[PDB]
Amino acid sequence: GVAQSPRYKIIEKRQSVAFWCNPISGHATLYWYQQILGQGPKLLIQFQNNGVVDDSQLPKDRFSAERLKGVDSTLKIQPAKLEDSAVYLCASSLGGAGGADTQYFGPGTRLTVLEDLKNVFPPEVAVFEPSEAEISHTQKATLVCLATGFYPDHVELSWWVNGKEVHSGVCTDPQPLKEQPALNDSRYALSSRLRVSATFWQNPRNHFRCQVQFYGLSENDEWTQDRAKPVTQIVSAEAWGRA
Amino acid sequence: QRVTQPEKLLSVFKGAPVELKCNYSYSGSPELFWYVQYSRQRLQLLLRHISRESIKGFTADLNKGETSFHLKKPFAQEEDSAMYYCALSGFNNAGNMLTFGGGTRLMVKPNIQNPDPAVYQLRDSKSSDKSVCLFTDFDSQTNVSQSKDSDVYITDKCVLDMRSMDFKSNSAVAWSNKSDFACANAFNNSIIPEDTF
View 1 (cartoon, each protein chain N blue to C red):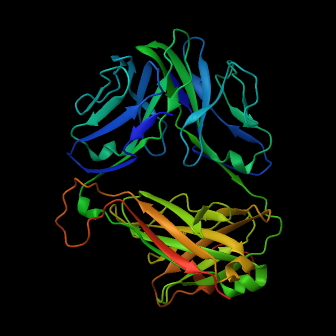
View 2 (cartoon, rainbow over the protein chains, first blue to last red):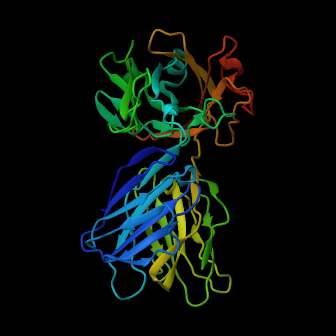
View 3 (cartoon, each protein chain N blue to C red):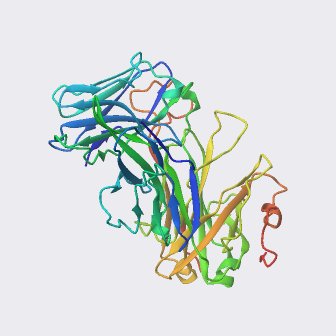
């Protein structure tokens, strides 16, 4: 499929940022879209081979794009504003001389523009063991994972049982909540459940891990604060079966 | 050239009909599409107006008298939960491009075979005396209201599928730092009178 890099990016206002897109081999048309949260994609620029076909909606004071050899393309924002926080989607289509062909999308780049990179925190993760009352009443056992104190909302949570990721029996909140809702720098918390049979939990050989992938600052970001640099990283918590 | 999806959220019961509304404004003969994005997947084409084929059970009929292209399915499936985008193609707008509507999220609620609502207390696996309150096994009638107290956190309801067991259940989580916080009082929202504590 179409490739895009990076998947997540944090930048400070007035800094610059570049996004990369590799279209489907041989696709003559390439599109860049901005998608604001709760909206649909809106075209930024479209290429036919290495030529700009539509750039009317490009915010030209700060946005620009190139596709110099008619294949891969770079979009850059210089300088970035807070309002540029969005998903940046790349797509390609064959570009044949007919009608509107099917557009094939990349996975997107999530851009978060912040006032202060010192507001970036990784999550702390805790796993809570099933209730004895639940085990007795339902013959089922629910584990809960809490990821807390992270900013910005750049997390992927997964569950691992005996070292293998599992999907059955799991539900993760689609949205985080704000730990301090009357604050626009507020850190976030997120919950997930994993439910197994009571006998599976009761087996002391079974291992349960909640994993949270956080996407934070990059290697090349400056950091002079005392606490650890809030880089992209995995934070996990674990629990063992009990009888 | 505009595409309007008038509602951002449609929540339906499993097996109930789905209609995701899309209206367009366009001078001439329009080309219309639906695109879909499932959780963690790429945005992708679902269907076009030119074929009558049902795709994943969905159809959409271009109705020029109503300038509509509504996406419809008679029996909602849990697998249909996703983001849906209507789109319209514009001829020689520099090239040939798409305009997207603003999206609608479809959420398909499970039909809980035997509601057994209860609030359980779970203790941290690390030696802290942190705990969480788990409200679970309630009917899809129940709505979970957000916390009004600043230092009590309550998540929305969430459905898990124990497909090995052919079993689905709703749950929501509540926790707090306070001395005062108890699961008997965690959810002072509209909960079932048969709720097990």
